[PDB]
Amino acid sequence: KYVCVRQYDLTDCGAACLSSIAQYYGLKMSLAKIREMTGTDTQGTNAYGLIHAAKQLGFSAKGVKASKEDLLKDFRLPAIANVIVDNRLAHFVVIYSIKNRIITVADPGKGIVRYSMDDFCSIWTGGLVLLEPGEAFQKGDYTQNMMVKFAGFLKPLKKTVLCIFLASLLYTALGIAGSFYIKFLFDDLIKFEKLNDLHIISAGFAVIFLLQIFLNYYRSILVTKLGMSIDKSIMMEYYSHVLKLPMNFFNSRKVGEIISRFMDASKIRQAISGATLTIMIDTIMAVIGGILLYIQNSSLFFISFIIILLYGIIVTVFNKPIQNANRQIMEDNAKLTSALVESVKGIETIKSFGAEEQTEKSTRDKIETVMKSSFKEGMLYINLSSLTGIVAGLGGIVILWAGAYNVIKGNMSGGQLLAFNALLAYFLTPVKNLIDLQPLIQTAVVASNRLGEILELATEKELREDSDDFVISLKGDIEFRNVDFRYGLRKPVLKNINLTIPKGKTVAIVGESGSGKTTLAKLLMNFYSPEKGDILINGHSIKNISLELIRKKIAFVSQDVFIFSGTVKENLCLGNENVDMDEIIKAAKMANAHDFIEKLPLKYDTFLNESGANLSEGQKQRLAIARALLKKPDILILDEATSNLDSITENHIKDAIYGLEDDVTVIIIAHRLSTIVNCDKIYLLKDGEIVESGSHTELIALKGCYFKMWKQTE
Amino acid sequence: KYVCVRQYDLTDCGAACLSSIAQYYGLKMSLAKIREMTGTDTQGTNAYGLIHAAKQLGFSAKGVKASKEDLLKDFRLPAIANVIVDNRLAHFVVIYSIKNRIITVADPGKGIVRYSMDDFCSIWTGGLVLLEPGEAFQKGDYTQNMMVKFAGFLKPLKKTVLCIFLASLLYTALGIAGSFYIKFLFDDLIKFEKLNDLHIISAGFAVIFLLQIFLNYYRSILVTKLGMSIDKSIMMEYYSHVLKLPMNFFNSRKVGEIISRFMDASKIRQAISGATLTIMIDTIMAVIGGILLYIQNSSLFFISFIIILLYGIIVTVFNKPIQNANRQIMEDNAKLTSALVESVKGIETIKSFGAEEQTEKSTRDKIETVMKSSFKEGMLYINLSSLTGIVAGLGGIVILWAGAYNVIKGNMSGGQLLAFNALLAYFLTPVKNLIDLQPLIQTAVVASNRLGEILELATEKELREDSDDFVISLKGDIEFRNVDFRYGLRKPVLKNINLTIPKGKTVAIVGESGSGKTTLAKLLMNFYSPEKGDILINGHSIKNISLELIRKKIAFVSQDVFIFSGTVKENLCLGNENVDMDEIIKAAKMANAHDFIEKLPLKYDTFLNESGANLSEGQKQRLAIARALLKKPDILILDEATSNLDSITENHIKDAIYGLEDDVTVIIIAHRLSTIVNCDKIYLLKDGEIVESGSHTELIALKGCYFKMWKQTE
Ligand SMILES: CCCCCCCC/C=C/CCCCCCCC(=O)O[C@@H](COC(=O)CCCCCCCCCCCCCCC)COP(=O)([O-])OCC[N+](C)(C)C
Ligand SMILES: Nc1ncnc2c1ncn2[C@@H]1O[C@H](COP(=O)(O)OP(=O)(O)O)[C@@H](O)[C@H]1O
Ligand SMILES: Nc1ncnc2c1ncn2[C@@H]1O[C@H](COP(=O)(O)OP(=O)(O)O)[C@@H](O)[C@H]1O
Ligand SMILES: [Mg+2]
Ligand SMILES: [Mg+2]
């Protein structure tokens, strides 16, 4: 069988292909784990990541660039081929069989498809990855059934589910009892002209219906409460786990990918609470209805069974094409909305270049594509509805025909036929719902896998080693031994930095843009870990210091500061909750912010709308600096904290942090060389290694890269 | 009556309040016209904007701060009051009546509400705007009916609407004829034991049903085609008008506000093609069904009429609360999504400050609020469904009861009762749909107004003056006369900006961040117009040159560069539709971009994913510079176009610009002073003024702000 693992996101096509190959060869594991192994980033994965993950997964993989002629030759069928769609997006596919000019490929985006050779090589890039099990490829099933894990949420709520079951049973029994009103009307009351009996029986059936309505009300309230509880539990569990995952999880994913998993909570709930309750109620409901129908007449029961069989066959046949059309519509709508967002976000360039006519044409073409996909799905739905209506109406007419024939033959009465028509609802609707549960359960299973593969990921605290409790301070020499680092599986950023930062000293790191300075700042702060080597504080390894203390004694002022929607009192007290106002005022004094914030409306409680969109960039930078010095750190890192600020405020903060109390280490990452000349030591980093060090005068005396940069920049 | 104009967006509370006041006083205008009159930006309007718009509208408006005791006294009741909603939003409300300690206020976000004086004063800021009509307040109704305007898309589609109407009439007639099968069964066939007649009549009714199904198929296909056509037409008209609007429309609105009308298009279409057709079909079909039911039996028809009256009353009663609950749910979901996006985007700061615990608490609280709103709406729906089910089921039971009574009394037969039960569908479903049209029509009207206020806005071309056809190029001295400017209604950016760029000589403009240099760059390109004075080229006013020529002969490289999703060639040729590859290569060389593009996969057709997300900042900026020089301009503006470049590329672009042929004017807006020294003339901008002009030699010698900044920044 050709395994085709669906891709959950837009950037895990290669991971999906590798998972498909592994499952075909007998190894099934989490797709999130493989996506971590392949070094998948926000820009998808590449061939090298696939080969590396296959090699370290047990396979014996290799890469090869081949033309169309090489495909005619013989080799291992299950290979991964890099393809390009629409002179556009680059995907990966799994070739499963090279037949006569026709190639079967599993594409994670679409499914199992057949491409003729010519168009395949038109879209297939020359790259190719060959896989084959090696010496150590122990087969396994390292994954867990995730519907059971989420269904375990029903254990605390067994009292609510039990009441729903009883209410549903009583509702069904009352409805079945009340469906015989039409039988009692024609066979007994109308025929014999009984009036008092008519009134009494009608009043009794009205009371029965009112009881049925009350039971439905109670059951609906209970079901709504159960669904809300399950939704809240699932969303809160997912969010609580996500907030603890390491930093390499957030930089390998987009905001949309993380946020969209919340809808998966409702998708799972719709089958955890809905599908199970529907099954339990409708199985007994349909069994009772079928027994009663067979009691009424066997032939009519068989006719109704044939009707429901035809309905189920039609629905099962139409299942997959409808979901394919829905996926295509979703893709087209995403493309159209992305184009609209891009064209309205860069409207200034379009206006300047006079491209308002071609943008309109492109948008119209995308709208046409969306309409074509919508028409395809609508035609599918119309065909399905027409077939279902034919089946239902012709079955009803045939049931009436056969019932009239049976009444004529004397096998049954007219009231019995009308009672059969009434019980047809209580027999067919449960089975109809049971059949219709199939599309919901598949979507719920997909969402359960998508949301629960993340829950298996180890958090940041679980990956840490054993910590030594005798360390209570981070004051001391900061030693960078031979440190390697690379963001995932890209080219290395840091190669052989080996430096020492003395305690209580103002140290500066300068270099070209995109050279590995912010990377060093994040490495010191324990975001990510060095691939090779160690980082030491006061002679102690960075891995042996508790994560809570390491994040509480190191303050960061990033290049792209972030301010959350809230009061200034809350934006300046993100971590701690018990802090005096005097400390906040003192912290804002050194950042040249208190005078600015005082001019704002009210006091240190003004709400910052839209992540501080009313704020300006320099003001937010001052706020971030104030927060950093408010944290009272042992090490303070300023990653270009004065890039936007004017000369006066920059000088003010420079003299403020220059004369700080206590032996608090200060590191300043600078792009403009003239900004800092008074730093105790200056480190020159060019392409991932330090080349020069010392005081500013010392590097000037020693002719080298620093002097050339100073001369060409000043 | 108390007028309460609801707000269409999140930033038009003050505009909605002013519109409500005007409508209360007899003047009705478009909300978009008022919104642009108030100077509403993306952060909303304030008291000054409302006062200015009211004075422009003929009112005699004033602004004053009021205390709690001030409300005790008497003043003009219809006044706008600034309030603070949930310590987050600076909203505006319209006070209408001051009753005994209870204040009636129209809030555009909620409706007409009543606040206790204590609670209001707790949520009411001291500010107050008093409005009163002046000498010139000629009333009117300066707006059009958007529903009638959007109903004009049915004119070319009058043939399709006619086919649908005829098919629906035939379908309804066939169904009404086929509903008598059960009447023929019991009164004629079963009673008299007719078998061959039974088979013949059953076959005939089956054929009738098949014809009905075919008619439904054809009508559904036509309806789908009609809906798709109308939706596409509305969407394309809206986008075509939006692309032609001035820039003050695009920077006063968010991206979401502009994009959200593409769903309003579908909302309008749902009533353009749904409401009219439903009315036309259902009125006639309900009339026929009611006449037939009255023919069958008068008392049962009256019972069914009472049933449908009760259903309509219940639906009308439950209309408003359901939509209020839905709006509340939408607001809460939007808040939760915004919080989730904020938390995910700023995960680095949360981790660095160890604030995962409190972010989880805030998200849980927002989830709880969402669940509360969801439960309120669910309970409203449960109550509505229970009442409707009671009415329907008890009506059916009562109809069966009264029909049996009439059959016993001899006023009708059993088959007549069964036929009445059958025709109950064709009588009750039409009126049910007509009653259910109310939520669709109101939402469609709101969406139509929202989408059509924009279409009344004047485009960029319509606001221009007469164009001089004798102007063919913009090569000449560029004179800024006494020029004032201010974005929207904020603090003015330029005061007396007066300067002269010589023809063909490279000139630089320097200053602080947020000083008003990019504003000058936009002003020279007809984005926005100066409040006072004129801008001239070669003695010709900027307002007398065709907008097509101005945008064609001026090239702009903004501080932020936008790259559109597409091949490099398409981006480099955004405006012109015809150009040879040699010029593209030549332009790329002088911007130091050709070498980078060569190393990319493919040569120049490399599609740039996600608006060029693959490229770096320097690569994007070099590509934009290449595009601008490819434009072949007469004036080239570089608004900080060398910031992200390294020194080598900076020098290459610098001496490429200095090596430009022809007398092409070059303007360079520079932040770093050292970046430009060789410019022919330098203008210094500090506060909306040029205080010092000249080359580097004289400006350094002359003591002033430029000398101080050069000394303190180098
Ligand atoms: C909650 C949602 C409910 C929605 C339904 C809304 C309606 C609800 C209420 C409906 C009741 C009122 C509607 C009319 C009912 C009688 C009509 C009829 O048969 O015609 C006859 C009624 O004249 C009579 O003789 C009266 C005797 C009543 C017969 C039994 C009716 C059973 C309905 C159960 C009662 C309702 C229980 C209420 C429970 C809901 C007239 O023709 P006749 O045969 O010649 O009459 C002989 C005497 N005569 C010559 C003097 C006239
Ligand atoms: N989040 C990320 N994911 C993948 N690669 C990154 C990320 N951030 C930076 N890089 C890469 O690492 C290199 C180092 O950049 P960085 O150290 O951030 O520059 P700077 O030191 O100027 O802040 C860059 O060339 C960039 O391509
Ligand atoms: N899109 C806008 N809407 C409203 N006000 C703006 C907008 N852009 C700029 N401003 C205001 O006008 C001034 C113009 O500054 P600007 O020329 O952008 O500075 P710079 O030359 O450093 O880019 C700014 O101080 C800002 O407050
Ligand atoms: Mg950086
Ligand atoms: Mg600028």
Image (tube, coloured by chain):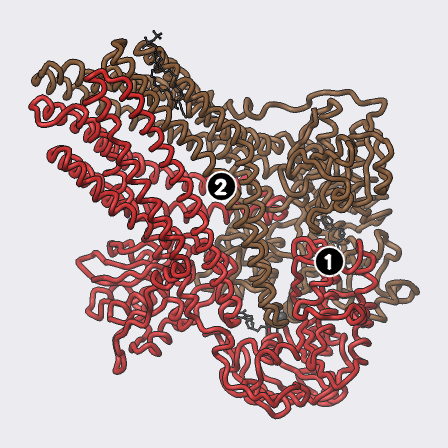
Chain colours: A red, B brown
Relative to A354, is A664 above or below?
below
Kind of residue at disc 1: Ser
Residue at the extreme bottom of the image, as rendered: A539
For the point 83% across and 34% down, which residue is it? B130
Q: Position of residue A484 (x, y in %)?
A: 52, 83
For the point 80% across and 49% down, which residue is it? B493
Q: Position of residue A155 (x, y in %)?
A: 38, 61
Chain to which mark 1 belongs: A
Label 1 neighbourhood size at 10 Å, few (<14), some (14-19), many (20+)?
Answer: few
Q: Disc 2 beta carbon < 8 A from ligand 1?
A: no
Q: Quadrant of ligand 4?
A: bottom right
Q: Nearer the viewer, residue B568 or A176?
A: A176
Quarter placement of the N terminus of chain B: top right
Quarter placement of the C terminus of chain B: bottom right
Quadrant assignment, res B358: bottom right
Q: Which residue is mark 2?
A: B379
Q: Which residue is mark 1?
A: A616
Q: Same subunit under labels 2 and 1?
A: no
